[PDB]
Image (spheres, coloured by chain):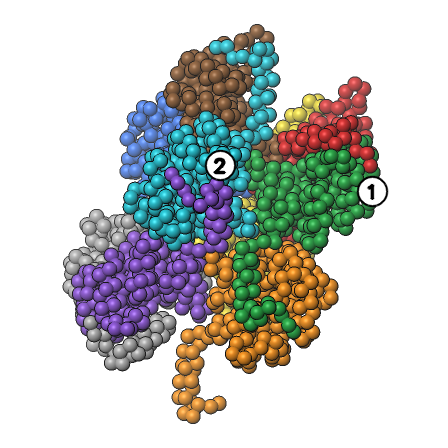
Chain colours: A cyan, B purple, C orange, E green, F red, G yellow, H blue, I brown
Amino acid sequence: MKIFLDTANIDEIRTGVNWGIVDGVTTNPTLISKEAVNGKKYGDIIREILKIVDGPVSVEVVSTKYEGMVEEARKIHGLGDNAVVKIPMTEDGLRAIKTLSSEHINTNCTLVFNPIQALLAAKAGVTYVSPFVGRLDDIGEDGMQIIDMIRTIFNNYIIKTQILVASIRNPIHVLRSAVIGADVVTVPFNVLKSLMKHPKTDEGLAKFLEDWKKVSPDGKLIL
Amino acid sequence: MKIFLDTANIDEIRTGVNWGIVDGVTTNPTLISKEAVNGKKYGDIIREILKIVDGPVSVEVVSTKYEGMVEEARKIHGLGDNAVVKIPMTEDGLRAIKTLSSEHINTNCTLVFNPIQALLAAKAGVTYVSPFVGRLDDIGEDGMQIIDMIRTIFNNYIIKTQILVASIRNPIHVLRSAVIGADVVTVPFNVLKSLMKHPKTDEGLAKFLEDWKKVSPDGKLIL
Amino acid sequence: MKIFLDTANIDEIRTGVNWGIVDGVTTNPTLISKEAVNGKKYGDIIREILKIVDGPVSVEVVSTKYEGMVEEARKIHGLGDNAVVKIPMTEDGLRAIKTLSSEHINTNCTLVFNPIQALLAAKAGVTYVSPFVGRLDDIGEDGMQIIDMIRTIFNNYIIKTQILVASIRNPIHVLRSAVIGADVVTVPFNVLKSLMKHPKTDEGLAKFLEDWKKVSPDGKL
Amino acid sequence: MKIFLDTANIDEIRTGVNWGIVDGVTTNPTLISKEAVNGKKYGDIIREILKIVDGPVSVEVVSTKYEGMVEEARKIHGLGDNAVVKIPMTEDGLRAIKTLSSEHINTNCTLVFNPIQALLAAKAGVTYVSPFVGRLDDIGEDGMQIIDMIRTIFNNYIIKTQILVASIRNPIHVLRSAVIGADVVTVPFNVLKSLMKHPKTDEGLAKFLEDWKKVSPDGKLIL
Amino acid sequence: MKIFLDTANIDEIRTGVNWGIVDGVTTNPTLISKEAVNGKKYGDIIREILKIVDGPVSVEVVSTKYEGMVEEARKIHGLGDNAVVKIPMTEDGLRAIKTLSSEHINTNCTLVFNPIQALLAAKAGVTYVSPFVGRLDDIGEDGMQIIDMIRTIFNNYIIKTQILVASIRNPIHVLRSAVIGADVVTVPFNVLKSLMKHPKTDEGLAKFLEDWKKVSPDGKLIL
Amino acid sequence: MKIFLDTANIDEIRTGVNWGIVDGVTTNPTLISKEAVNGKKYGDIIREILKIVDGPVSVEVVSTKYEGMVEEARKIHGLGDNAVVKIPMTEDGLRAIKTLSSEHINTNCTLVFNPIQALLAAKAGVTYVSPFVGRLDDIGEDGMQIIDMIRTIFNNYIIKTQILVASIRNPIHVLRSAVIGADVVTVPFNVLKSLMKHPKTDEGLAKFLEDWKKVSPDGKLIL
Amino acid sequence: MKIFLDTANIDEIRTGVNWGIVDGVTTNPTLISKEAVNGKKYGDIIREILKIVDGPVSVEVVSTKYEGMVEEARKIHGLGDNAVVKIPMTEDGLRAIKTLSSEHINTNCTLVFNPIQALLAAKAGVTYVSPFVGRLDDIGEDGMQIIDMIRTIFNNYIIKTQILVASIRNPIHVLRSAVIGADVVTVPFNVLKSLMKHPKTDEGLAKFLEDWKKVSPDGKLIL
Amino acid sequence: MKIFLDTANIDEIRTGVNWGIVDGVTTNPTLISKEAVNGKKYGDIIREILKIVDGPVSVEVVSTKYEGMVEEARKIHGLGDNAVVKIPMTEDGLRAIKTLSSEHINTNCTLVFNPIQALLAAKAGVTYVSPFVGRLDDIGEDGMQIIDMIRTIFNNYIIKTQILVASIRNPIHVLRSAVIGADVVTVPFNVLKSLMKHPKTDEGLAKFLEDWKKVSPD
Amino acid sequence: MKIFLDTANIDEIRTGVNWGIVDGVTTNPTLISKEAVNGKKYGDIIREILKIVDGPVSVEVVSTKYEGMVEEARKIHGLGDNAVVKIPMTEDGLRAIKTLSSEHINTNCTLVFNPIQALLAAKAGVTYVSPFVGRLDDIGEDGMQIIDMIRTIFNNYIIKTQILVASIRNPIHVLRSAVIGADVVTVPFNVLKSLMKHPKTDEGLAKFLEDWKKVSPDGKL
């Protein structure tokens, strides 16, 4: 399972990449808006992310119309080989995906909330689909069940579109995604950090340290 | 999973194909007649669809007897290599399917209501079998269960006949067909249009747009 | 399981009632306004339905504010003892349901789309809760799963609020509702009229008549 | 799933084959003793049923002893390469099957009533095993469960012996056989006919005819 | 299922109570610390909550020692009949619960992370146990499974202690609690608010309003 | 679920009882001998436990023959109305249990390793049956499965003999016993002590303490 | 679950009863024909087996016809109120059971091999039904599944007929009977003896003896 | 599924070999001692079985020590290429199996009663492992469950060791072994014969005979 | 499934190796320091174990910092080709594993308590991951469930990291591991020595000897 970071915050990205556990980044217009404040420009933010991340970086078009989507998508693609064009699940969006796929431009269909939307995006030839599990949770429906269904549907038809679980809120979204076999999860930084941690890991390390001090007061391993 | 339209309206066909999620077309004399207005010739409508659609277009034979069915099926086949001849599940229809299959004329066995009917049609060499799920629902039997059994039977024997789910009435017939692994669904243009929609898609897109305006007043993405 | 008819069409209601299988009626502002055209007034349509139907008849408030909702509810109640006040699942709606329940006015909480909304409506004291299964189907989610969860939740807490399955589109919503154990279904007329029918019933009746004529040429017993 | 006809009555093969859903024929001493009356000889019977069939015809030995069974089997064989010799599940029967299998004579082990008897016949090299599901039903045991176990056992060991469901009494034996994945079912000509029928099919055809008459009051599709 | 509000924020409490959907309140030392700032005293906050909430209000002891726990618990109890003394799952805590239960003082055992801790608290006679599902989620374990086990254990022994699901983070914690049959959930205000909402409710109300305007331009129901 | 200690140490007993989660005591000659030091009389230790414990204390008979077992059991019973006589699953032990049960002397059938042994002991009238789960685990068989079957058998026949899970080695034996619905577990004092612990309990309590100090410098709760 | 002894051999009742685990006895013509040799008469046999048993003794009629069966049953009865008359599952058998049940003579219907035969015997008023699980095992059918179905059927209808599992061959027939909830099992005296044994029991006793010798080198518990 | 005959009785083997439904034979010291009476030598009993039986013949070493085991084994092997050396599940036995496997001498590890024992035998390179299901039944545990677990474990690790179900007591042990997918069952003679029988087969043969008499009075 | 011995006790290791059923050894700082007493040096204990054991031998770094971890890892590797470097599940640990994997030094990620930690370790390229089942049991959670999830996750992504079940306390952890399909178990000596044994094996051997003596009074073949 690939793990992407879901943020436009450059510090978070630099940090996660250096932990070596981040395989790509997703952004969206909200995430970018949060960073493009106090004189910081969205164009600079987008270019910098592409620059410092080796894996896929998703950048969303803002046009709602077919022609605007493809125009902006080709611009995004032109920014770097690792750029992936996010396109929303709409009529114009599917048309754009079909065109962009025929142009060999990688795409990510976003704002997906049920399995049939995911299938339609896959049929249009999208590279990734991004269902928003947390926003389904928000409305009283267990979002992970939609990931399970998408995985089954894709398996049925040997679909190569990657399932990219998005709107992740907690480490159980991550665990269930892995158990289901989703291709990718994209997670906020605070979630990313939490995935490494466990109280028994902390406790176990402290105990090993204490016991070792008995055999080596300076705490070193001299071999 | 392939998606066919129950329609004879080229505008709908063109639009669905442009979305990249329509793989062929299913017709009947009524669907075609519907369009034969304001100078439109019944025959031109069918030949126009055949020419424009890269994939399959099902057209029903009206004869009820073997000889009439094969003569009619041959005339249908003569109109396009992608025409598929729709033949009902009857004793004479099975005989017709067997003959036509040997002539390498593609076929679609319709009015299928249980899995053994579907198996017999596959044994005669039929290209597609079309169970009518909504008509089972109509009589208080869950039509999708018949699709599930047909998928299992066909899988057991590596049967190459495609399951074409028909009499579809709602997007859950579509969802369940995908999860089961049916080869094809055929749907009205409006059922088709509904398949892309979700209120969280609309709300999410609206919030993205609003947030983007905060950093790009004219709503543009200049890259 | 009770079976209600989901319509404001008087002709459909008379026909269904005459069949003997309609236990009540549900209306909503869309259904009523569909009928209230070409001269017909909504107040007349609502009164007529109340008169015709012996069983519960759901009529929805239009106010979005608590105060307006309770005022309209009391007027609806005043129209006849079989009237049931439909109140939407909103903050003001829950307040209104609680007040109306205390005044012993039967209520029906509508526009319910998940099991927790249904539980909130029950906690407010609502008489019926009406989840919309077909509208969930419309957006790619199996609406009947919500009914199954609501039945389990209500069973767990011995909740007396009745589960009223609404936005029904086909006879399988009805079958599944019965297997789950929902208290009520409300069905459009076209669905209602299909529930008694089966092709093997028709065929069996024909066969029985055929065979009986061999006994009595005239066809009587 | 292959479908054989299970009768000795010539009136009840050509037409089944013409439907494209008949793969062969079976019989038995009883079924033979039914048509070998009023001047018709069993010799004539069995003959009339080999030349025309592009498939398998099961013919049952009457000898209860090894030498007799094998002698009979050779005679039966001699009548054609597609002849299949039916041998009961007995000590001598297993011996005969092993010998005949080594002589490349095709065999069908009948009177099988549990899964271990089926395995034994397979181990002796039998071409088909025929469990009698209806006779298990007669004694208050669901016969189809035996077919399910045999399927599982044969799958476990990649056994090439074909499961031939016999003593079929209704269309649900047929349905369940297909869902389980039995290789073959043998059914009387009439059960066979019932398999294609459904009242919604009849209804559907009448609807199609009615509506075609609207499009074209004549009753024929001119193309 | 009872729904408590998990907060010490007086405005949130007043608001939730007036929605009529809140049956009680839980606090803890962190929650209170958040409010007891800028001159506001914890004693005043606690008394005000007890004052304005009719249902149970949980207030946690801060002593870690048996004698301190019971001293503080009796003080809390003395503040009002609706007060429930929160006691942590520790050795001294269980001793305190046993004593306080014999004194007819309602108790709530908190910081519970597995089912056997819950059982021990129930054996000591506690009125509620409060497992922290979100903090289990935090460490990569699905916290709702612990609620399921506790429900089964309590059902087994007809235990009257109430299961109070705490550390709730989202509406799916709430939904799963209800399906399991937990006695109580305690939720933060933002979660509380979300439970009432659904996009199709909003959409449905807007449509009813629009349609009604056709029949009554002023939008009123005059009866 | 009742909890017994495998111990003869009054300090442990007193402590566990004070926690409110110990319902009785199980002993053996070794456990008792352990404590018989520094002037301590073997006999006084057993009589002290009997007097102090309100509930049950199991003491094993050492005779292997019927007459010896009943004479010894009577002497054990004479020491306290709460003494329970532990008798092994043997032919003579069953005879002894039947006799003793008629004298209304409570009994505990030990060295039970399968569910039918447990059923026979219940049929003889035994008060408790003690399956040794850890000793089954020792030989590569999951001991808790035997507890599960005994619970089902006892439930089937409304058997009033209590299932006393013994040879417990870890807290999961305890958890599984509770989920199954065993009547009693017997555990060493240290297994018992471990049952209350969880690292999230410790961390949570520490954070609560820290947060409280922010508003009450001396860490007190003055109410 | 009641436990009967299934033999006609007097050497193989007093001791079973003394263990407190025997509720009664059954026999049959074969088992009788085994002990009625070398000068012993069946009359003597059956007698020696009624007076001493505080329970049920099954005695089988030999007549195959109604009048004879009922005549025999009265004689059998006359020997004691606890006598139970064994009647085979036949047309005349069902008649006899109905008559005897109306005369308040207790009956046991034997030679039952499927669940519907069991139901029929219950409907005629039989006191016990005895399915032969081992003889089903002999013919490649898991006999215990029949007991499971009978249990379910009897539960559905609150049937008071007791299920008496017969033709028991091993301890797992006994275990499964108990788990299913059969009312009774009848077993030979030896199978009976095997039921109490387990090698870990033997091992455990030896351990206890060894360690007792440490506490008290003498070998006796002085209390 | 292969089927072996589990006996040391020459008459039974002969009768069963004559059926041609036997794929091999297992013996053990108990069963050998049964027939090694009335002047009969165990050595004669074994060479005889080996000669008559084409398939694998399991013959058990009697030594309990490693060195006595491999020497015994090597001499059992010398008696015929179809000989399979039966070695018990013990420390020395595992070591002997390791040595014998490497010498390309086929082995059968016996007295196995749980799945981890069976795994240890497979790790030693054993050709067959023989769990004793009936002896588990005897002590109140369903023996077939152990076979089910061994099949799963062996599947997990693509283990080539064959599962040889032993201590078989009835035809349901056999049926369940087949459904699980055990490689081999070994059965006592009375069990083997019963496996072909069923009352509806008998009733069926009779009816066919009766009806055939109508068609040809012969 | 490989079976490793979890101890730094030389006598236990020699004994287990001589039995032929030990495929490797795992150590940790607690196990080593237990042995490194009354004059014994840890460097000598570690070297001795490496010499005795043919299979993989896990030896844990003590540094908590990346740089220290890699330095110590290289020294451990230098002690013998069978050495496997144990690295804890921490941020610095994952970095160290990635670097060491690139240098073709076998690694074992330890102190793993949930399936996502295990996945992170695999993504870093670790040779083995070692979840601690008994320590999960200690805190009231069935540790084996974590192994089952890790096996499923690893299967889904065709992950080549070996699952090494650690903190094993009884033979059922071992049985369950095998049924799940874990690649390795590491077991304390007391558990190791129980795996070959069963009371029915002992009884069957006794019976076989008894019966054989009736054939040969001297007891040979």
The answer for which chain carries disc 2 is: A
Residue located at (40% from left, 46% from top): A87
Q: Is residue B184 above or below residue I143?
A: below
Q: Considering the image in quadrants, where does the N terminus of chain A appear?
A: top left
Residue located at (78% from left, 25% from top): F42
> What residue is pinned by disc 1?
E79
Q: Is residue I5 among the parts visible in the rendering? A: no
Q: Position of residue C16 (x, y in %)?
A: 54, 78
Residue sticking out furthest to the top: I39
Q: Quadrant of residue I141?
A: top right
Q: Are marks 2 and 1 in contact (CB under 8 Å)?
A: no
Residue located at (22% from left, 70% from top): B43
Q: Is residue G109 above or below residue G48?
A: below
Question: Label 1 neighbourhood size at 10 Å, few (<14), some (14-19), many (20+)?
Answer: some
Q: Position of residue G125 (x, y in %)?
A: 60, 67
The answer for which chain carries disc 1 is: E
Q: Is residue I79 above or below residue E161?
A: above
Q: Three-letter amino acid code at disc 2?
A: Ala
Q: Which mark is residue F205?
A: none
Residue sticking out furthest to the bottom: C218
> What residue is pinned by disc 2?
A36
Q: Position of residue C100 (x, y in %)?
A: 70, 64
Q: Is residue A209 among the parts visible in the rendering? A: yes
Q: Is residue A87 left or right of residue F82?
A: left
Labels 2, 1: front one: 2
Q: Is residue A196 left or right of residue H74?
A: right
Q: Is residue G62 left or right of residue F174?
A: left
Q: CA distance from mark 2 to mark 1?
A: 52 Å
Q: Is residue B148 left or right of residue B61?
A: right
Q: Three-letter amino acid code at disc 1?
A: Leu
- Mark 2 falls on what kind of element? loop
Viewer-side residue, H110 vs E146: E146
